Length: 124
Image (cartoon, rainbow, N blue to C red; front, side, top):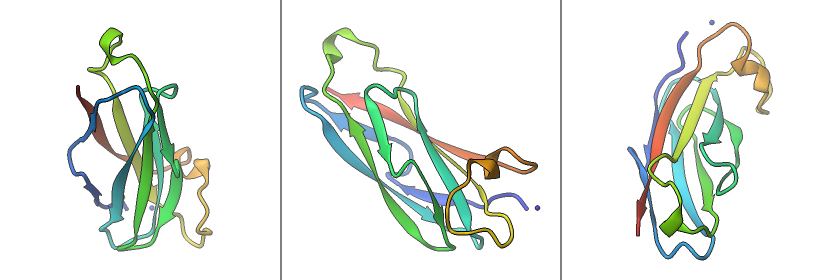
């Protein structure tokens, strides 16, 4: 069982959502598996009501990339909290002879889970 390797994301440190916020805007994040091993990944957000990611989980062979769609619903920016949103990429090396189909179990059994945060920044 070896620690999960590194991924590369685009954008690499954060994602900026531009107003207007009266419409749903769909952004994209590129996740690349730079490591030498197959990895399973899950995506999480701090605001299920406003934020959505798709696909929310998957598998990535070495050097394979996936393009995720991060949607941001319309909302009243002018009256809400916006200094706390982030998208979280979690991943682990896929166990030996496992299918290219994501199992939440990979993150619950003995092993290592790695994570990368991508804070959301609002440009009003």
